[PDB]
Length: 193
Length: 48
Image (cartoon, rainbow over all chains, first blue to last red):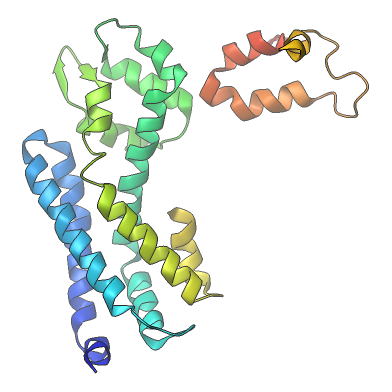
């Protein structure tokens, strides 16, 4: 009774609005280092939101009505979901590139500080991020002085707070894929994630 | 450990249909490991 009532309720609209606000707020708070606590609290709220969805999708048969409703909601809120997935994968690839050897020979600094220009050249050599992504990563990077960036801290800044929300999103996507097969629209989200 | 010798030898792909492997590995792992590092490991010349 309660699950069907929520399914027919206006909850979805609220979900779409929260997705929009989350997607823009995480991107804005990432740039400034003084709002890390606010970013973590936002991530926790998003985690609780994904938990509620997961709970709304309890005990559904293959091709369930609630499942198709949530797929329709996702395709309605495609842009924000793509932004959030891009936010996760950019930092994942940033961690991998920081660990990679090419950046190690690019930095050329015993102090462990990478210049903005050299960082841009190293990313353009790795050829994994688009130009706007390079600019956004540079903006999020914190240069103490003379454009010297602490790449290790920059990479590890957003790792721990974003672990739970990423796992919840992955679990939700896996459940939706395994319970709603042969859906062309969901495959886009699956391949973006 | 013994197979490490023919990595740089020019005649590495002998007795095997694909003689363009070295190029394929260069194009596959050039971005991550480094194009110059791959060239040194495989004994190839980029300009050539």
